[PDB]
Image (cartoon, helix red, strand yellow):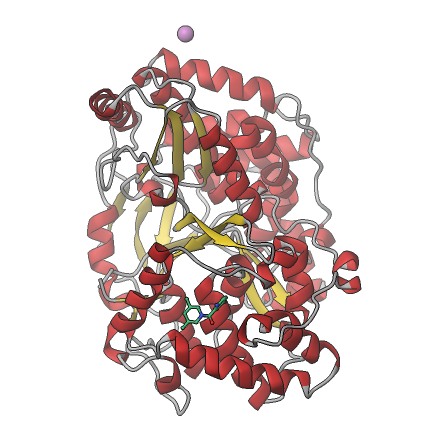
Length: 557
Ligand SMILES: C[C@@H]1C[C@H](C)CN(C(=O)c2cc(Br)ccc2N)C1
Ligand code: NI
Ligand code: NI
């Protein structure tokens, strides 16, 4: 029951890899401590292999089978449709990895006959063959962080023609089933504001609240063949077309449960018997599995009136305190239960009695005041990684723009507003590139977004108050200011000064550019403009934005 077996062939790169922060003429205006920032590369892939490779034991009790029967009961109410090849093709990202069979993402997206014809052959093969393990590629991810050095994460993915096939059979299921099965507990159904609202309401719903986040050690690697078969049995509860049932059975047997790993040079690297990081079911399967194990462990631990919020492998529980010493014991039992279910902890969970101090999905609730003076809750996070990534994107073009996703998700925040908007607006102004659509990711799915649509996008997701928050909490202010020291980023007084300039330049452009100046930087000027509902915002087609998680799933919306 080892998570992985290995040949000793190396995990190899596709192109040359950069680990040090690329530097240009714009770098110093953002950050001076260039050595704090790095990108992971295949050079550390061996250290990751070590970490992810382990024996899994699972003991499954009555609480577990009880939760699952309940889940399947809910799953039986889902009706899900097959996608046409064409619909599946339009969900493929433009920069998704090319097929080994002589076509790429551009070909799939164009609906070309070489691509489409191959995808059809892959589909027919899935219908006819439910046993032969499907080939996959293993790679080291190149990802950017600030020190305190992580080894590269691994991505494991099947060929392009198989990914399109997954969309056909499962895209509707993974999009629909988790909310139905999990209700209010399914995290990816919420905008950041809706998330805050859920955590706040939930917290307020207990006489003596206590909460904790649960950090599973390498979750993908803890996921067993049992876990995967269990997920498939949930999928099959849906009302599906016969071809869909057969294709799902096949993908589960041939791909999801495990398979051979091939490097970029075509050498056999070993064998996977755990969650593949790069398949469509990655987010939905982790969420369901995490929910099943956690819900059962809550029963084993006898947590009182617990409420969970789950996003893939990210788990937060809020419940009724039974006192400081009883809570610590409860959490021990919870952790023992999760371990038996093959989800042992990284850092062991600790009970928290302040909502603002609970971190889940790398984020926490904080408090600011709106234009009326009223305390308002909002979602923030520690800015270190958004800024390290922003430093990289200042000097390099990337397929996915972190800074843009961060402005979108963290728009009400002190640091997104003063640092991210100012800095990137400055850059795009200077290159007359305000009108250029850029790719970014939200809950794993990729979106092409025009920076000039940011006021409307923001109003529609966070509301007009995102443009007027002030008097941030001493705790938030100081985490930001402490992040700026560590990175060597100019202090906020500098950013305020720069934003006034950026604001004036944007206004001078007229049109959408002036809207960005008006709405995004009103915080920067003492003589404040009247911020009214933007007409275009109500016309914005933001369906499928905050519906499901697609991390690893090769989705383009
Ligand atoms: C805590 C920050 C410290 C900085 C010097 C000035 N300052 C701001 O410009 C500010 C920024 C935003 Br965004 C909202 C309200 C504000 N008063 C507040
Ligand atoms: Ni065995
Ligand atoms: Ni029972």
